[PDB]
Amino acid sequence: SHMPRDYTPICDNIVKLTLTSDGKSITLYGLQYGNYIITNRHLFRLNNGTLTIESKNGTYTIADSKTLEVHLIEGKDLVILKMPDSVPAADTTLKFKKPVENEEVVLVSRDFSTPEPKCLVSESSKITPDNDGTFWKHSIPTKDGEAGLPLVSTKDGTVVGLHSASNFNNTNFYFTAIPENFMELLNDESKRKWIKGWHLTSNSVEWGGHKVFMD
Amino acid sequence: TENLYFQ
């Protein structure tokens, strides 16, 4: 028996990032946590751009991804973005935990299109680790550009991972698991190592015992 | 194993 849950607090902290530079953009989702935005590493396929963060509070525009300070999660398609101090921070109400096998998750998505936003909760699905643990597999159909959307456990309502990649036939879907002591990484600066100008210049990346493409 | 593409 698991407690019935309202997923609206998690929806209120989902943000839509769009890194645009010279007519080419990369749009995927993220999560708002204080002065930080947790999102996928493959958001930075291009360097020197303009980040557009769309939150429930407002829409923000940021100077140059090269100057941006980012903490990279080791061996995972995850990155912590340090927003400049002028941007208002979000709630620290989001709860991150390492996923547990045989624990069901639901993809929580916010629909920015409709005049009234919809806190969408997908159908439940089990999770299993893939190869070295860089990727975790779920059975929730995800459209393109839906990476960074939170995988939320139905037991305790914690974000256990963010969506990342899928196969070309769109039959298996892989998300990036939240690492151990990830909440310790958010509230303790001594564990954070910030880097600037990180970008993914390569077309093909070899991650998680797989060959992942950008398109 | 199987090839993937980012989303």
Image (cartoon, grey):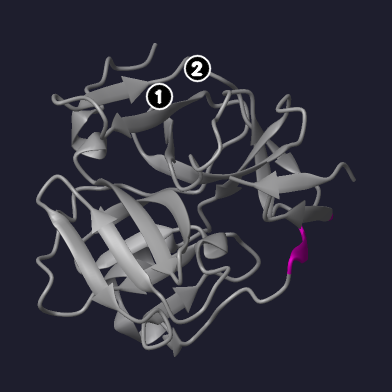
What chain is tagged by disc 2?
A: A
| Residue on which the image places disc 1 | A154
Query: Is there CB contact under 8 Å for labels 1 and 2?
Result: yes
Residue farthest top in this picture: A1
Picture coordinates of residue A123, whole percent (x, y): 47, 14
Q: Is residue A58 something that shows in the picture?
A: yes
Point out the residue furthest to the right here: B1
Judge whether A140 appears above or below A146 on screen.
above
- Give the vertical position of A153 relative to A199 (above or below): above
* Residues drawn in magenta: A203-209
Say if the magenta span includes residue A206: yes
Amino acid marked by disc 1: Thr
Image side of residue A67 versus residue A135, left or right: left
**Residue, x 82% and y 55% (percent of image)?**
A211
Residue at image x 50%, y 52%? Answer: A178
- Is A174 magenta? The answer is no
Q: Is residue A156 visible?
A: no
Amino acid type of the residue tagged 2 in the rendering: Ser
Q: Position of residue A90 (x, y in %)?
A: 15, 57
Disc 2 is placed on an element classified as loop
Q: Residue drawn at (58%, 49%), measured in percent from left and top? A: A176
Q: On the image, numbered disc 2 is attached to which residue?
A: A124
- Looking at the image, which is closer to me, A73 or A22? A22
- What is the quadrant of residue A156 in the picture? top left
Along the line of sight, which residue is nearer the eye, A21 or A199? A21
Residue A3 coordinates in the image, percent (x, y): 29, 17
Q: CA distance from mark 1 to mark 2?
A: 8 Å
Instruction: Please check whether the numbered discs 1 and 2 fall on a single chain.
Output: yes
Which element is circle 1 on?
loop
Which chain letter goes with mark 1?
A
- Residue at image coords 32%, 22%: A120
